[PDB]
Image (cartoon, helix red, strand yellow):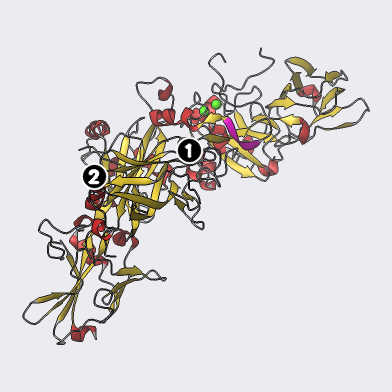
Amino acid sequence: SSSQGLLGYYFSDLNFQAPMVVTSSTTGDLSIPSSELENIPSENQYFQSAIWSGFIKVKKSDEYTFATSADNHVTMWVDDQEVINKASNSNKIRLEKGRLYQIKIQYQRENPTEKGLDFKLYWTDSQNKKEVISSDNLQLPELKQKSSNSTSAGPTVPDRDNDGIPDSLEVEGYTVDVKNKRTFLSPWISNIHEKKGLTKYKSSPEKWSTASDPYSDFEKVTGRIDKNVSPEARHPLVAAYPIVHVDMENIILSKNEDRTISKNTSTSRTHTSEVVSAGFSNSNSSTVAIDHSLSERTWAETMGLNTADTARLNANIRYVNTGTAPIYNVLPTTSLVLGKNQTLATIKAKENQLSQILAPNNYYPSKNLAPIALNAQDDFSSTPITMNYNQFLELEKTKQLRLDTDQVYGNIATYNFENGRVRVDTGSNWSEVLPQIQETTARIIFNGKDLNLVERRIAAVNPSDPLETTKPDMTLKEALKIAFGFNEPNGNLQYQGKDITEFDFNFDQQTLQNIKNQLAELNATNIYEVLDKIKLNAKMNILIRDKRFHYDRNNIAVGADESVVKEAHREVINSSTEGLLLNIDKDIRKILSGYIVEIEDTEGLKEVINDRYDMLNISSLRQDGKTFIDFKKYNDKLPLYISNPNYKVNVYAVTKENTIINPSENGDTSTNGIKKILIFSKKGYEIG
Ligand SMILES: [Ca+2]
Ligand SMILES: [Ca+2]
């Protein structure tokens, strides 16, 4: 436990005013060699005062004499009783086993001749055995949030919220740097720390956790935190909390009786806009699209499902955490919903019986393991998921399901100062924390990574709330850098090489009005030029999306402009009568449902090879990540027959938003009404 010990505050001044280093020491050796002070101006490497705080506990009752390597400069209290005061002494104090004695030490030396501090806390037993106090006998002060209803003995570091960071540092700015076995927390000094690659922190001196999450500002920056918490959420202004949805991977529909439809499904976590404007809702939901492709006639007929029959549904799922904190003992409950509000099933996992962690940016079960079946194989008491005839017709019509997941996440792994360890705390519940996170942060949702919606929350002021006014200012620019890792190599804001102007900015109706007001005040008509001047407030909702795609009402990417789709297919690696091989970006493939292949004769007449709405699925991804478009799949497994070399092979792309998933009113099953985009056209002789 390299984080346990006494907590020390080292000041350059004589009167505990200018804290230069805040760090813990594991043993009674409270020294800081000048060698580990390279992030401190040499001039300020002289410590004229210091304060240490914590507890001492003993594992064998005895009478003890405390001594220090500089008693003449030390005043020391044990449970508010003064035991050393500017003179060495041999007074004994009885220390009882299994008790916690509060320790406080102050040190003052004017104008020391050495940089740093050489200082040790000793004790002597009843056997006259004197030694530097061991790591086993020391523990940190309890830097947890106090109660509403929460003397002296010496100097007090102003620390209104009891996180451990002095009020002045949180307000004016601080940083941390790891030297060997320790993390030194120091005031921000621009002329040293910028070119050392250090991060400048500010936080609220009134909020134990500035993001209102369950990890203290001090715990976050000193690494006294769950290792599974996302690295961006180690910043005191970025909230650390789980965000869980269910991903359905495939589905099997069957008729209930004493022939089946088995289809892959694609599932996306959603964010439902209002009317144009981002939504206010913080609920977890995902929408499932069932593959409409060919396996003949309707599913219902294939299953032999008639008016008085019932259909059964089974599926494989995983839980996905797209948040910034892990989950340990409770997976959230999920409703499987048909249409608007027809609940087909309640999906639950057993409380306190998780087989593994559900970590940020990860899955439950993990990808190397089998997914969860809604009705497991040997689980014969599991409730079947059934639907009547009408309900099944509705399912075949929409081929869509919804998964509404609650926000019940179980207990939190928190740091324990008693033993200097992170452990699951049974008295801490994510439900006791989420509402405050949601109430005190601005939310940004960004899809730049892979077009999936990723949500982050950033501590921001509430100008109506006195406590939330004590927070550091937060610009839109800074939030994007700290929460999402946007950067700016030459002062130009980017996300992973991509210019900021490539992304659209959308807000809820309240946030929009706020932003427009700020723009008018800045005499700006464009948000890009003033991203570093736009201020965020608590409860803003900001949606940021790649401009190259079309989005549905759930803000899922479902298409792109014709030119974007065409350009994406310009890179043909190989063409033959068997198919096309080409490089297609991941993001473009995400918005395509498949392709239509046609042969056009010299007269301009056409033969469509795969002429069914449910025959678009002729594209596959190779191991090397290239896309193969298979001409043979729906051509009776034969290469195209091109009767004359001057005939053309035309291949069209179909985007998700233009995909037809059922025959038309009149029973048309062809591709004739499908809105399609030409992406390849070559003559027989050009193909070879
Ligand atoms: Ca504080
Ligand atoms: Ca704080």
Crowding at mark 2 (Cα within 10 Å: few <14, some 14-19, many 20+): some
- Bounds of the magenta segment: 421-426
User: Residue 407 in the image: x percent, y percent?
Assistant: 42, 35
Asked whether residue 598 appears in the rendered view, the answer is yes
Picture quarter with the C terminus: bottom left
Crowding at mark 1 (Cα within 10 Å: few <14, some 14-19, many 20+): many
503 or 509: nearer the eye? 509
Q: Where on the image, by quarter, is ligand 1?
A: top right
Amino acid tagged 1: Ala
Instruction: Please give left or right for residue 112 compared with residue 596 in the image.
Output: right
Badge 2 marks a residue whose secondary structure is loop
Would you name the residue on which mark 2 appears? 553
Asked whether residue 489 appears in the rendered view, the answer is no
Instruction: Please give left or right for residue 120 compared with residue 668 in the image.
Output: right
Would you name the residue on which mark 1 appears? 240
195 or 268: nearer the eye? 268
